[PDB]
Figure 1 (cartoon, rainbow, N blue to C red):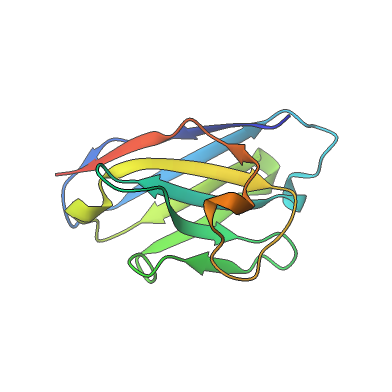
Figure 2 (figure 1 turned 90 degrees about the vertical axis):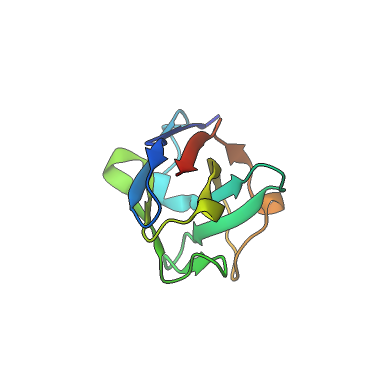
Length: 127
C-alpha cells in the first residue's frame, strides 16, 4: 500500500555531511507513527546492510557499527517523512541508500528481513 521515495542523494566531499529524506505515500487509513522505519545501503561490491532504524512504540533507535555517533535517524510524522543525517562521510559510505518501513517493531538493529515496504533508493557518492 505505502509507497516510499528517497531523495537527497548526490556527490559530497569526504569529511562532509548530507541529509537524506524519504517520503511515504498511500495507506492514509494507517497512522504514520505506527510504522517502524529504517535506512539501509548497498555499497558497490557489497550486500545490502542495515544503517539505522527507529522503532515505533517508544522511538528507540539503532545504528550500524560504522555509523554510530556519525549518523542520526529522525522522522517528521506530520510530513510522513523519514530523514537521515550523515556526518564525517568517508569513501566507504558511497552507496545507494534505501529507506524501508514496516508495521511492527524490533529491539535491536533490524536486518532487511524485518521490513515490508522499500523505496527505490538514492545514490550517495563520497569523493
